[PDB]
Length: 358
Image 1 (cartoon, helix red, strand yellow):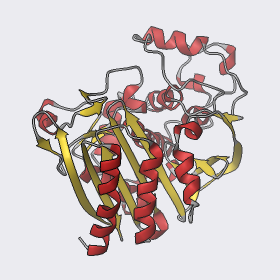
Image 2 (image 1 turned 90 degrees about the horizontal axis):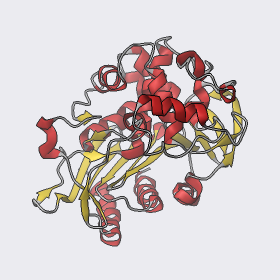
Image 3 (image 1 turned 45 degrees about the horizontal axis):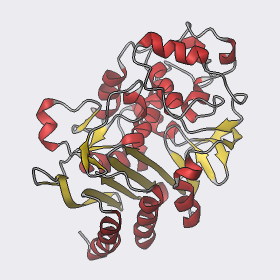
């Protein structure tokens, strides 16, 4: 642990924890490709369990990065194409508003106004069909971006259909296992419960509740070690031996749409490096991140740019996570916390750390 990294991380994260009253936090910095780990505070306040490198945190929407890469892997396998109509994989989806809505639109939140959340009322699979059949777009496909669990969540479910695997089985066998993410889970097994941190929301210990398309949109739990390895794999996909997964990673960092200075990937979001920190910091606030914005199609998509800030924020009711990396500098960070605290604080801290190391 070079003193520079120690000092930079501690000087930034200590005040963040104090200001945001975060109960527990783990941070990994990837510097010249190698990970360095830092932990603070409590996984479980009541039982006095500390955060360790083995603590599992809810990733919330950082999960979308795994879904985007798994979709990418399915494209690379020749199982799906992003240009395919959604109805090719869900023939029961016969309502006319779906004409012209492709898997690309689903993956990138550009289908025309699919809502942020699947309604809590949608419990059964027939409920889910009804919901999509009845949904009315506000906009033509590929014209506006509206960040949405119901959009990429459906992409993930459809993407694994030709494999015949459940979403969880496909994720395990095709992404987690080959990458040796052996402490990353969609459903935490009983053996790992001792490591599963509680999230804290208004002082109450909470875990994410089951919901439709949860696995696909926000349901991954992982350790800081596995998340560092996830960043390493995304920094350098060519080191990955499994050909379709290497390609999948590359596809997820391709640039499909532009809004303002951000580019939409599959799960990942990207900006040119060097970035303007106000732009990524203010841009991460849900006031902008969850807003409806016109998009410019990137025709054809630009392949993964190495000089990019690639990142994703994610939260559940009790957790707040952030991952960011810059391929061309072999530099990244993962910040996992068991409080959902404001995005701009996460991105500010990440930028202060990476900027100092870059």
